[PDB]
Image (cartoon, coloured by chain):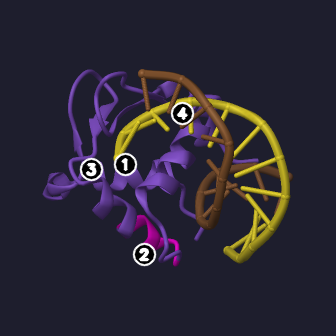
Chain colours: A purple, B yellow, C brown
DNA sequence: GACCGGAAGTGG
DNA sequence: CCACTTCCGGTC
């Protein structure tokens, strides 16, 4: 797979029919996984990695902290916030 | 349990 | 190369 997790989360987030498992909620960029497990099995599907689970996916998100692509929303389960500072950069090619 | 981050490894 | 994937030893 060549798609990126943040890109894929957005894809999902861009249709509200997927709200049964992920949804925008809060200030600009915030969202929460209403079904963390379905999100993971989907990402797994998409990347042909079928042992994907939330514990692994969440690790990948944690890596995004240093990249400023995302922060954790503190004291809110399964909630993160996209940050534009780093998205801007990750949208740039070579 | 959830969340954190180090470390090794992987495959488009 | 690099963004993950896998796994794990810690904090609550």
Q: Identify which residue is drawn at 54% across, 62% down.
A: A3
Lateral position of residue A8 relative to residue A24, left or right = right
Q: Secondary structure at mark 2?
A: helix
Q: Which residue is mark 1?
A: A10
Give the alpha-carbon distance from disc 3 to disc 1, as whole Å: 6 Å
Image quarter hosting the N terminus of chain A: bottom right
Query: What is the crowding at mark 3: few (fewer than 14 residues within 10 Å), some, or many (at least 20)?
Result: few
Identify whether A89 is placed above or below A56. above
* Magenta range: A42-48
Q: Which residue is mark 2?
A: A45
Location of residue A25 (image quadrant): top left
Give the quarter of the image for residue A69.
Answer: top right
Disc 1 chain ID: A
Residue at x-position 36% and y-position 68%? A42
Which comes sooner in the sequence, label 3 or label 4?
3
Image marks 3 and 1: residues in contact by CB distance under 8 Å:
yes
Q: Which residue is mark 4?
A: A69
Same subunit, labels 3 and 4: the answer reads: yes
């Amino acid at each position: 797979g060549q798609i990126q997790l943040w890109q894929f989360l957005l894809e999902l987030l861009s249709d509200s029919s997927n709200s049964s498992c992920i949804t925008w909620e809060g200030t600009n960029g915030e969202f929460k996984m209403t079904d963390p497990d379905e999100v993971a099995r989907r990402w797994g599907e998409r990347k042909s990695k079928p042992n994907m689970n939330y514990d692994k996916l969440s690790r990948a998100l944690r890596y995004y902290y240093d990249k400023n692509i995302m922060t954790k929303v503190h004291g809110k389960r399964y909630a993160y916030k996209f940050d534009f500072h780093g998205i801007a950069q990750a949208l740039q090619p070579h």
